[PDB]
Image (spheres, grey):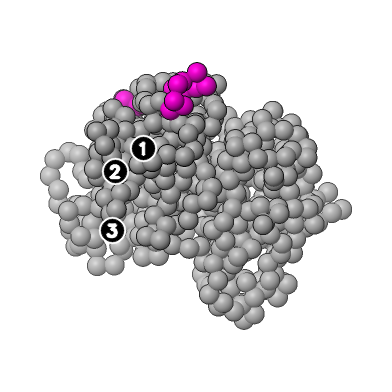
Amino acid sequence: NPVRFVYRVDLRSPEEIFEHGFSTLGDVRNFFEHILSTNFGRSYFISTSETPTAAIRFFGSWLPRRAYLYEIRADQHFYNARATGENLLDLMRQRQVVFDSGDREMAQMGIRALRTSFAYQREWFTDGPIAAANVRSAWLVDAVPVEPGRVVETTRINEPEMHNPHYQELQTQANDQPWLPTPGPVHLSIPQAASVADVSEGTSASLSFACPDWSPPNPLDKCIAEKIDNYNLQSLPQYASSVKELEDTPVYLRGIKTQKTFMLQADPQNNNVFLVEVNPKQKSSFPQTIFFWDVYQRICLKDLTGAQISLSLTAFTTQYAGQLKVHLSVSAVNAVNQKWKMTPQDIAITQFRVSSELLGQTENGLFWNTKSGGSQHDLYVCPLKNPPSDLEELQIIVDECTTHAQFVTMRAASTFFVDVQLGWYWRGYYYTPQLSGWSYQMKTPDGQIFYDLKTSKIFFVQDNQNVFFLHNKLNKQTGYSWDWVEWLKHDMNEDKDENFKWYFSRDDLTIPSVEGLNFRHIRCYADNQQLKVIISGSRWGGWYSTYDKVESNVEDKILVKDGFDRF
């Protein structure tokens, strides 16, 4: 599915933006500077967001304030930031980049920041300005405060949609190529300083989002953010200092009808999410398990498992049609079924409807079955229309004796795993890699094979307590220039050993394939050992790395989940 529309929150009114569109603040086309907000205000790129939720996150800083959420039609001069950076990482690793300024180590610290701290921005950036014929609508967003008695608030996207009569449905779509300075040796300039907007909760924003109302003389006084910080690249922290103010909170929900109150519970041992009825005000008893809601819209279980993984609320389909059931799975940054929205439902702003991004535009909420026995209850996602008469909506209750106000804002992420769902394809058949180093004939399941954005390691989750890392063995002393790869237990935080480090390449590949498949080449950081699979013979499906470019009867196109390099 192509990107047709993007989003951008602005202090300016449709009045202006509807006719002027969005003007660049400069002439410079330097990617790293745009990303890192280096000497801010000079850039030829305008930053947009693949989702409204992402676009307005900066506006939710803790300081009614109001601004305008614009819906923009995307075309061939809109480029995804994350995918653009991954392609440059590939070029640097393959050593085909000439460095006008700075070096590769520094560029990689920037790519790191892009992949982690800034990634939730779901940024699409325009090469040059956005015509008013591009802008299509606008909404009225304001920020109201959560249950009055640092003050926590929520953004609201208000009715009604205001249309731009200068817009023209041109049936275009965002550019699915990564951005390059000289489009058709690539030359790169890497800055030495970064700027970061601290939009509360440890969250970092680039100025190209947090300062939508920029113009030279102090301009920073018009940045919606707790503060702006400056760093040398080597000094750019993962979190903003506001991360230190994070409160822990259990989650309480209340039936719309019955008025019964529940405490969210989750069990990392079997991945169950369930509900347990509680007397409000009266605490203690059942263990108050802790959840947070992060900038990837995930609702995560508080701590990591023995294997250093994170678990998030996941909306699973069932054996029963339009029925969704909440379970835990491994926090993944691109898992749409892990993404939730919260929107207040009462004037007092104490009740929040939780809806799944998985049902896109169909309004939906959380439900339980008001007739179920036992003491623990399943949790469902249902559309708000014709919901079965025996279920009722559960909404998050944020009052004195329930959920803390901090929950209903999006805080910084504790983990940055992409579900890459690696596998391979042979004439209509799908293969999944096994821990043994072999393959098995079946499409790789969701939520099993990951790429850790912090470290560039790839891992295979056997279960919440057992994680294995892909490990290269080949070197210049290996006769024949190939050797098997293997899966090894390893520390999730270990960041020095290059044999555990992998990256993805587009190279010459047709993307997507004639048959719709997302293929990538995969190589090791250490010495560019390429990852491959033997297609047949007595060792069919054996995974290995090689230096040998020209081979027979092996597959070098690896299936990687669509979007893995966009989130």
For the residues labelled 1 and 3, say whether their Cβ atoms are less than 8 Å apart: no
> Where's residue 80, x and y in %?
58, 54
Q: 290 or 419, which is in the foreground? A: 419
Q: Residues within 10 Å of mark 3 (few under 14, many from 20)?
A: many
Looking at the picture, which amino acid does disc 2 mark?
Answer: Tyr
Q: Is tag 1's residue or tag 3's residue first in the polypeptide sequence?
A: 3
Q: Residues within 10 Å of mark 2 (few under 14, many from 20)?
A: some
Q: Is tag 2's residue or tag 1's residue first in the polypeptide sequence?
A: 2
- Residue position for label 3: 382
For the residues labelled 2 and 1, say whether their Cβ atoms are less than 8 Å apart: yes
* Quadrant of res 117: top right
Q: Which residues are magenta?
A: 464-482
Helix, strand or loop at disc 3? strand
Compute the Cα span from label 1 to label 3: 42 Å
Q: Residue at x 59, y 53 (%)?
A: 178
Looking at the picture, which amino acid does disc 3 mark?
Answer: Cys
Q: Residue at x 14, y 51 (%)?
A: 371
Q: Residue 431: which disc?
A: 2
